[PDB]
Length: 161
Image: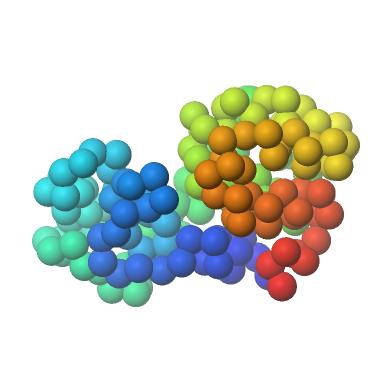
């Protein structure tokens, strides 16, 4: 298992514009197009990202292209000054869980997780897992949150197998 397989499980793959769990236009493998309520705006964001007039539909290769880009960008944000120490302190599996979180909620979302982050940095897994659960994230997307949380607690891929 790896990050790509991991996220593909959590996000799915849709080739036509859809609405995510928050009601935002998305396409492919969890690729957020816009927070705006205009589908027009979303189609335009799509053509721009893709580099062609799509008419809200893409190919599987194009979805995989966006995905690769997105994983690399998130890995980039993890080189932040606030995030870097955490990510660098982690083992390979747990780093995958951190990427997942950021992929799903952005920098801005992962921001209110200071306390949990601190606990992960200290390798207090069970304690972190409890703290991570006290969050809107958990209440809103509980099945995904649990898989992620189990991954940080165990350092294995069990939740995904």
